[PDB]
Image (cartoon, coloured by chain):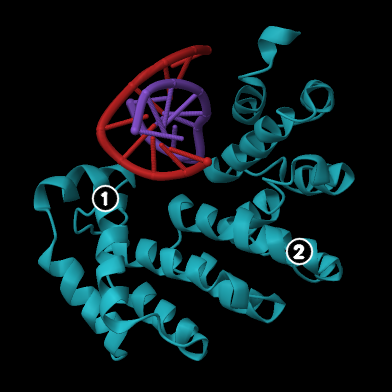
Chain colours: A cyan, B red, C purple
Amino acid sequence: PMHPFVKALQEHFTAHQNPEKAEPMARYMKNHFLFLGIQTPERRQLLKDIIQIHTLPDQKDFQIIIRELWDLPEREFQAAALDIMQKYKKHINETHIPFLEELIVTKSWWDSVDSIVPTFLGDIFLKHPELISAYIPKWIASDNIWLQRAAILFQLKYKQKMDEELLFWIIGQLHSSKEFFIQKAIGWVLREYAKTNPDVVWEYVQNNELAPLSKREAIKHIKQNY
DNA sequence: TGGGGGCTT
DNA sequence: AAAGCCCCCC
């Protein structure tokens, strides 16, 4: 934690770790990560304490801090890094897409990736429509399952802004994936979109090839209506 | 299947 | 802030 802010945060988090909570938190993530055992309320308070002391670092340092936290072993530091990224949301723009790509493909799991994609990337592509073709096809073809999940979920919260043709194209490109988290992402985005346009999702699921898992996930809340 | 402490609003 | 939702999990 070269940067003083990251050092303080690490010291403060470590001083407040809870071994009894570490185990179940770690199991939730299929043991891919060590945990300190600090849940979100306390994790955010501990971040608040440090901000109260140091003040939020200048925007020129924000990528440095986030990377340094990403390199720390315990998962809470990546969670804290995302809390921090949210506080800098107004300074995050299209020039940061490569930075966000690195975050997605490093220490990858659903918890970090879902926290990056629908909000930060979703907003970026809304403001910069021309960049969709520069990133989405590349992510789909990358064979990195987390970039693939990113391509599927960037429109997750769009509601009526959903580009249906694009969504169905992206899903079509990944419908044969044998990856659990891709099949789940397809199910999720379809299920979420069905809150807005259930008819189109129902017809899509009935008439197109998807894993049974994705079909089950997609229709779990609307099947009682058909 | 379909619903649940941890999270959100 | 009482109450709904659930990425995920099983």
Identify the residue under disc 2: A125
Which residue is label 1 attached to? Answer: A39
**Whether marks 1 and 2 lie on the same chain:** yes
| Residue A187 on image: x %, y % | 64, 34
Question: Where residue A76 sits: x, y (%)?
Answer: 30, 61
**Residue A49 figure quarter:** bottom left
Say which amino acid is labelled 1: Gln
What's the residue at 22%, 80% (across, down)? A8
User: x, y (%) of residue A9?
Assistant: 25, 75
Q: Which amino acid does the dot numbered 2 rest on?
A: Phe
Please provide percent x and percent y for residue A95: 68, 82
**Vertical position of residue A100 compared to residue A28: above or below:** below
**Picture layout, residue A110 above or below residue C7:** below
In the rendered image, which quarter contains the C terminus of chain A?
top right
Which chain letter matches label 1? A
Residue under the point 66% across and 27% down: A218
Residue A57 seen in render:
yes
- Say what secondary structure mark 1 lies in: loop
